Amino acid sequence: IDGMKLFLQHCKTCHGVDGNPTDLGEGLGARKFADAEWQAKTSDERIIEQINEGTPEMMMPFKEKLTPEEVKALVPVVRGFK
Ligand code: HEC
Ligand SMILES: [Zn+2]
Ligand SMILES: [Zn+2]
Ligand SMILES: [Zn+2]
Ligand SMILES: [Zn+2]
Ligand SMILES: [Zn+2]
Ligand SMILES: [Zn+2]
Ligand SMILES: [Zn+2]
Ligand SMILES: [Zn+2]
Ligand SMILES: [Zn+2]
Ligand SMILES: [Zn+2]
Ligand SMILES: [Zn+2]
């Protein structure tokens, strides 16, 4: 499982690789991942739940597209470690 490959396939269109939302992402309500305060206050579980369930009118759920292993592999990408 390549976490970054999954991110480029499924997430990049709203959350850019640099840790900054795209124009589309920001319009829907996304904020920066590249933020020390956000990273410090956000648990892995919150990240996993967000990928799994999304947010109505903002982010689609990915639970029916990705396995728990694949969702977990995305955590160190969101964290900025690749
Ligand atoms: C645009 C249609 C999006 C795609 C594709 C992905 N995400 Fe997203 N995400 C989007 C918005 C508008 C928001 C804000 C909504 C909210 O309730 O916070 C988000 C949010 C996140 C978060 C934040 C959770 C938190 O508690 O702050 C994470 C960690 C996140 N999104 C990750 C993520 C991943 C890994 C994706 C690919 C599988 C992905 N998102 C797709 C918009 C969009
Ligand atoms: Zn890679
Ligand atoms: Zn895929
Ligand atoms: Zn997709
Ligand atoms: Zn980002
Ligand atoms: Zn802005
Ligand atoms: Zn900050
Ligand atoms: Zn962690
Ligand atoms: Zn819990
Ligand atoms: Zn709990
Ligand atoms: Zn919750
Ligand atoms: Zn939310």
Image: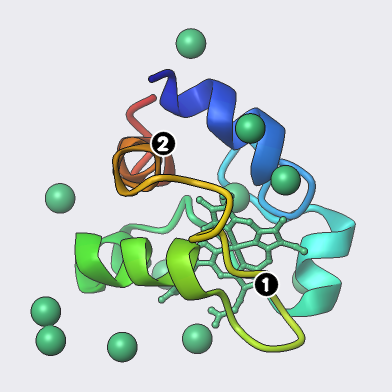
Q: Badge 2 local density, few (<14 within 10 Å), some, or many (20+)?
A: some
Question: Which secondary structure lies at badge 1?
Answer: loop
Say the numbered circle drawn on residue 16: none
Closer to the camera, 36 or 76? 76
Q: Residue at x 79, y 46 (%)?
A: 13
Whether label 1 lies within 8 Å of ligand 1 gets the answer: yes
Q: Residue at x 64, y 51 (%)?
A: 20
Q: Is residue 3 above or below residue 45?
A: above
Residue type for callout 2: Val
- For marks 1 and 2, the one nearer the N-term is 1
**Which residue in the protein does label 1 denote?**
59
Closer to the camera, 55 or 28? 55
Q: Is residue 2 above or below residue 17?
A: above
* Residue 27 point in image, percent of width and height: 85, 74
Q: Quadrant of ligand 1?
A: bottom right
Q: Nearer the viewer, mark 1 or mark 2?
A: 1
**Which residue in the protein does label 2 denote?**
77
Residue type for callout 1: Met
* Residue 30 point in image, percent of width and height: 66, 71
Lateral position of residue 55 relative to residue 40, left or right: right
Tag 1–tag 2 contact (CB < 8 Å)? no
Whether label 2 lies within 8 Å of ligand 1 gets the answer: yes
* Residue 57 point in image, percent of width and height: 76, 86
Question: Which secondary structure lies at badge 2?
Answer: helix
Residue 39, quarter of the rendered image: bottom left
Residue 11 visible (yes or no): yes
Residue 25, quarter of the rendered image: bottom right
Q: Badge 1 local density, few (<14 within 10 Å), some, or many (20+)?
A: some
Q: How is the image coloured?
A: rainbow
Residue 43 visible (yes or no): no
* Residue 36 point in image, percent of width and height: 32, 58
